[PDB]
Image 1 (cartoon, rainbow over the protein chains, first blue to last red):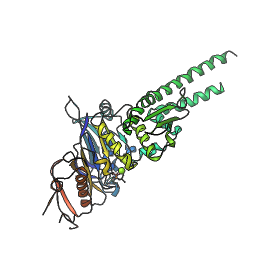
Image 2: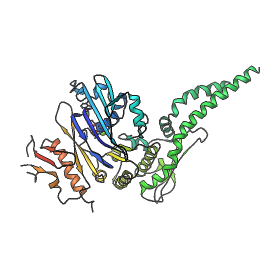
Image 3: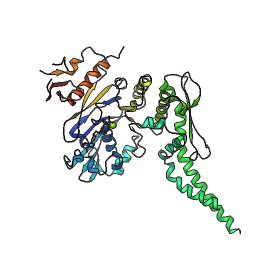
Image 4: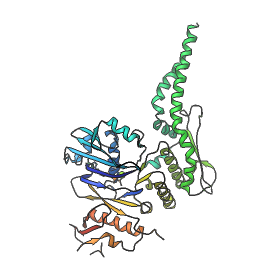
Length: 360
Length: 58
Ligand SMILES: Nc1ncnc2c1ncn2[C@@H]1O[C@H](COP(=O)(O)OP(=O)(O)OP(O)(O)=S)[C@@H](O)[C@H]1O
Ligand SMILES: [Mg+2]
């Protein structure tokens, strides 16, 4: 279903208790730069259980409003989300900072992080994969990635890499490897091939799904049926050694690798690769931090319209945006504004866009 | 702001506009509150947004 609303108290730049939203299918967070737009994405992934290490602070208490000044506003900070689902009633997830401890609740039923997670895990939300978010600059980091970097990118998300060095130690065990030696060399083959498959499968459980969707996604982003994307490995036997080539045909253009496309074309394929990644094990809502910073005048409307369409079909779209061309296709705006204080103080406004007509 | 100079309704400033013009007015409430040129208030989510002149005057 969808993230219905967000409630926060004293989280990062957001002082006091505020309601954020309620959210619709396509909602855009806007505001002046540096006022705490990203911090709102932190609050979401905080309440979905993110490790303190991945929320841009050193210690958990630093998440509490005012810690950057040495003046934390309280001993107690929290974020909660109301998840709405068709046929079910609303459930409430909340995460609370109490001194140095995190405390988690579901409809006030206190739980441990484990039970908190597996309940979010069955809604389609993987705090390990971070399937529900896209960090500022992700697109252009993708767009610059070479085939071996692309393989690496698949390896970490698929958890392929965890077994990658116990693979290296048993391949090292086999290169070095009178009949009592033939039988131990037989244990080498078994011990290696067992790891060759473990890693092979982890990689392919993930990569093969992305590869069949990327083309239909590249078509929809282009808004042109003459577009084609291709994702395949340089080592179909052992994909996690070589690279992942990425071939595209841009509309009214010739077939060629993604790297040789023009900047405007590179980013579109990079979005296609991105959405195809999140096409693997997809989240009910999708959170994009300033995806539109990479975009230029031509294709800004094309992805705004692709997201506008996916919001009523495939997932709730919660998008931080800095370009009026993108965020004016939203159903609603959450405008962030700053008050004056020792540190920055964020507060939100809510604007309905459906009350007004599209532009000429 | 200049024409805007006693309290102001956002939903009235957006009478008869299209999306890009209303989003523009909204976005300008944010920047004016940032620039202290106004204060503002909103009762509940998606209600009218109301601006009274702010500590840095007109
Ligand atoms: N615990 C905290 N208390 C008060 N302020 C904080 C806290 N943690 C972070 N901040 C501040 O939150 C402010 C806004 O941070 P962000 O949300 O990342 O800004 P932003 O709007 O995303 O900026 P961009 O990406 O340049 S447009 C930062 O300047 C921080 O100094
Ligand atoms: Mg940011």
